[PDB]
Image (cartoon, rainbow, N blue to C red; front, side, top):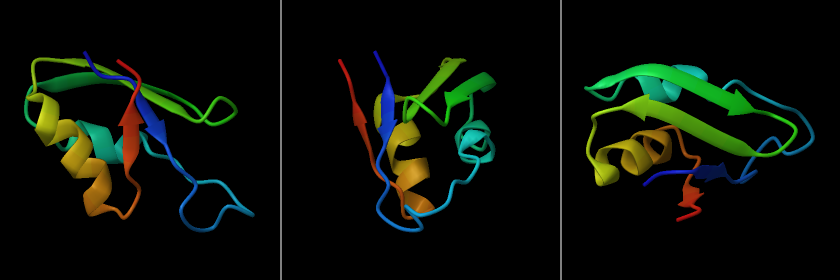
Length: 66
């Protein structure tokens, strides 16, 4: 399963929305993020690698806590 710990690789002095990054992956229809907990959850039928690669496309990797 997926549980993306969005790392603060850059702009760690600020915050950004990761939600728009997750939806771009096919099969994703719902998304939920917690800017305070540093986590990014989705609810779709996408592939495991497709999700974690999509956020890396924005330059923000995320440790699947699974």
